[PDB]
Image (cartoon, rainbow, N blue to C red):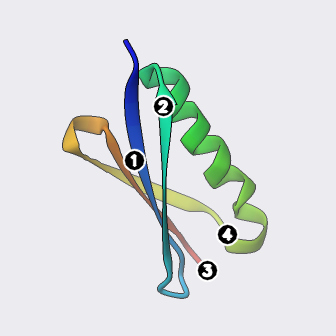
Amino acid sequence: EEVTIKANLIFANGSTQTAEFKGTFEKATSEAYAYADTLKKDNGEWTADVADKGYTLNIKFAG
C-alpha cells in the first residue's frame, strides 16, 4: 500500500528540483500536487506528465 512518488519540478528558468513523497498512491501524489501549488505564486501555473507507471511526476511551470 505504501509507495514512493518522485516529483521532478522544472521551472521556466531552466532549473530543476526533485522531491519524493511516501505514502499511499493517493496521499503521496496529493502531497506532490500541493507542493507544486505552493510554488505557483512565484512560478506560474504547472502542467504535468507521468513516467514510471505513474510513480514519477514531471511537473513544468510556465512563466
Mark 1 → mark 4, Cα distance in angstroms:
21 Å
Q: Earlier in the sequence, mark 1 or mark 4?
A: 1
Q: Amino acid at mark 4?
A: Gly
Residue 16 position within the rendered picture, expressed as x and y whole percent measured from the top left: 48, 74
Assess whether mark 4 and mark 3 are in contact (beta carbons under 8 angstroms). yes
Assess whether mark 1 and mark 3 are in contact (beta carbons under 8 angstroms). no
Please tell me how crowded label 2 is: few (under 14), some (14-19), or many (20+) other residues with Cα within 10 Å. Answer: some
Q: Amino acid at mark 1?
A: Lys
Residue drawn 62% across and 63% down?
A: 45
Q: Mark 3: which secondary structure?
A: loop
Of the 4 image quadrants, the one containing the N terminus is top left
- What residue does disc 4 label? 44
- Above or below residue 3? Residue 7 is below
Please state which of residues 58 and 16 is positioned toward the viewer in this rendering: 16
Mark 3 → mark 1, Cα distance in angstroms:
23 Å
The mark lying in front, picked from 3 and 2, is 2
Please state which of residues 10 and 3 is positioned toward the viewer in this rendering: 3
Q: Earlier in the sequence, mark 3 or mark 4?
A: 4
- What residue does disc 2 label? 22
